[PDB]
Image (tube, coloured by chain):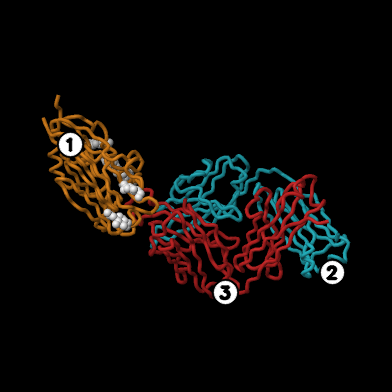
Amino acid sequence: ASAPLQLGNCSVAGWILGNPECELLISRESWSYIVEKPNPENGTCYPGHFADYEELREQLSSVSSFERFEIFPKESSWPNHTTTGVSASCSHNGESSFYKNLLWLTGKNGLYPNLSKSYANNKEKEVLVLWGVHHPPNIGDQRALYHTENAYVSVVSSHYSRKFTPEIAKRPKVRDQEGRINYYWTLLEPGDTIIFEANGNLIAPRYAFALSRGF
Amino acid sequence: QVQLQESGPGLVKPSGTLSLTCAVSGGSISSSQWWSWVRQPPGKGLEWIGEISHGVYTNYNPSLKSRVTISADKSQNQFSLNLSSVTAADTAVYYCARAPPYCSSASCPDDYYYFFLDVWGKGTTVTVSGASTKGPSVFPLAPSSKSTSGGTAALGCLVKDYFPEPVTVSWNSGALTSGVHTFPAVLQSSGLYSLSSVVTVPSSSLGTQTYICNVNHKPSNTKVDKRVEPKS
Amino acid sequence: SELTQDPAVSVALGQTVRITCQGDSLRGYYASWHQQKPGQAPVLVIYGKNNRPSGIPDRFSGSRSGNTASLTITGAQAEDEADYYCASRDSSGNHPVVFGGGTKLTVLGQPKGAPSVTLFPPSSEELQANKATLVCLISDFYPGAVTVAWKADSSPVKAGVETTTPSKQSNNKYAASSYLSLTPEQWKSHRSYSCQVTHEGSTVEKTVAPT
Ligand SMILES: *[C@@H]1O[C@H](CO)[C@@H](O[C@@H]2O[C@H](CO)[C@@H](O[C@@H]3O[C@H](CO)[C@@H](O)[C@H](O)[C@@H]3O)[C@H](O)[C@H]2NC(C)=O)[C@H](O)[C@H]1NC(C)=O
Ligand SMILES: *[C@@H]1O[C@H](CO)[C@@H](O)[C@H](O)[C@H]1NC(C)=O
Ligand SMILES: *[C@@H]1O[C@H](CO)[C@@H](O)[C@H](O)[C@H]1NC(C)=O
Ligand SMILES: *[C@@H]1O[C@H](CO)[C@@H](O)[C@H](O)[C@H]1NC(C)=O
């Protein structure tokens, strides 16, 4: 049939990002509309702003095809960087976890060389790519994680082009997190190529979503 | 992978300035890691001195901040240690080690809240006395029938009268390790150290295998290679 | 904000021992454990919160329950006899590094053996330098409690004697060295010199003579 997508205690944010508690029955192939709660409990476990949330929340309302794929393999695409980053705020069953669709790239051997990863959308469908940018509360943690203080994150596509810089500032304490991670998303049309170049503070994507907005 | 190597004078006059250098291969001083200095007095525990991150950022022990400076040389991949107004309480073995990056706030991955020193150096001995150094005197220890227990013999070298610590003794230029045992030096009443390095070898290899001890004393720049010959 | 350990603790072979390291600074950073054998640099056995480096046996394990960190050695072996220091960072100010007082771990497996005494007379080259020194070498004795005595022609001598404290050998034993400094006249004018080694009731004596 075409029943609605039930999110339960989860919001669209934690659902699409891969919140460690929002990873059950969410692999549904198609749905007509989304049903959540007036005040969801599980979403962005790591505090941060979700850019273009309403736009994304409306694009994913009616979906006819929906499958996720490892756009960047964890054990294959990040040799010089550490990928096993886990946060206490995104705890799951008494264990510090992280988003399953994103990767917290940090330094390896005290070094963070600039990376350049690209992806060609050869799937004949529209791909939803999501990424984050970390903002440490102090510059001491900025150097500990990414080795550099002048970090840049450039995300360039055929229909998207934006550069990011960290705003080092001590935010209010939310879930024992005085830093922030801003979440950004874009739709990659068939044939488009998205580029990721960064030297720090990049929350790299792991699983994208090849979808098609239909009935 | 990462290897460390201290280098110093081995002897500093009181109220002087100690200067060491930790050469690092297989790693980068300029990294986010904390390249540290740790000392250990004779018969006491480990004491933390300081550390240096990147090539510029430092952190020191409050008990000795007023006279310690840790610098880094990114060009030669080395970082040094400076300690002024030295006293007798500063005589110790000085190690350089590598520490992980850490976060001051609770907003980081869990792997950034460790402290440990996984990579250590061999450590260099530094003595604060004010007495001029003295080169060692090497003498052989030829065995006989009394030094043989049927098929088990023993022969070594005698390193008499030197200052200060340490003295490294190898055999056949590192071509022997079985049965070798270098005894801890003794501090005689005069003020000079003396140790003896012996190697337990069988008695059926006396008129065949040649034995030579390689005594080294860096503070006085002395390297003597004496041959241990049994005579009638 | 200080780390405290037990000064010494002992364990028999195959038994389990737990070394406790207490401190208020253990509530902000994980606690590591470093092993130091005599005459060697420290070796890291626990990264922290029970994480071992490559090459460390799994019989080492860590644990934390609040302000206390514990290193556990299951089925202790002879080569585990060493010093153990805990470490972390203080959670106040510039975050200094705090070390523990240390813990001398003594393994009490007893492969009891009698010492092997070897007495060396002064070398001929040393006599030409107007010097003479006897070298009495002791090795392979358990436990490491021993007393040395010197005799000159069956007469006790105590002047100019230097004896080192027993130290652990490579094969998990003990070894020490004694020295008797004397003038070249005393070496030649006497008949013989002896080195007595008293180890747990028994006494082994070795004698050399000018020849
Ligand atoms: C998904 O949402 C639930 C809320 O329904 C989250 O549970 C919350 O988890 C945090 C962290 O474990 C709890 O905070 C801590 O609570 C303990 C007491 O158990 C307290 O001692 C600590 O100081 C801290 O305040 C919070 O109470 C808890 N909320 C509820 C209602 O139980 C869960 O963490 C969320 N998971 C994800 C992945 O977003
Ligand atoms: C989900 O929300 C409901 C709201 O009534 C709550 O009772 C339930 O405990 C929540 N789920 C979990 C796993 O806490
Ligand atoms: C990458 O980093 C290296 C190291 O500093 C620098 O020399 C280089 O010019 C950087 N290149 C880019 C494209 O960021
Ligand atoms: C990792 O380092 C190698 C060696 O310089 C480099 O070729 C590679 O591009 C780096 N990885 C990434 C993702 O850039």
Q: Chain C shown in which color?
A: cyan
Quadrant in the picture for the C terminus of chain B: bottom right
| Discs 2, 1: same chain | no
Alpha carbon distance from label 3 to label 2: 38 Å
Q: Chain A shown in which color?
A: orange
Q: Is residue C210 visible?
A: yes
| Residue B225 drawn at (x, y percent) | 67, 60
The answer to whether the residue labelled 3 contacts the one labelled 2, judged by CB atoms less than 8 Å apart, is no
Provide the letter of the chain coloured red.
B
Chain to which the residue tagged by mark 1 belongs? A
The quadrant holding residue C130 is bottom right
| Discs 3, 2: same chain | no
Alpha carbon distance from label 2 to label 1: 103 Å
Write down the residue under mark 2: C185
Write down the residue under mark 3: B13
Mark 3 or 1, closer to the camera: 3
**B224 is higher (above) or lower (below) than C34:** below
| Disc 2: CA contacts within 10 A as few (<14), some (14-19) or many (>=20) | few
Chain to which the residue tagged by mark 3 belongs? B
| Residue C56 drawn at (x, y percent) | 52, 44
Mark 2 or 1, closer to the camera: 2
> What residue is shown at x 19% (from left), y 32% (from top)?
A66
| Discs 3, 1: same chain | no
Ligand 1: quadrant of the figure: top left
| Residue C150 drawn at (x, y percent) | 81, 60
Mark 3 or 2, closer to the camera: 2
Q: Amino acid at mark 3?
A: Lys
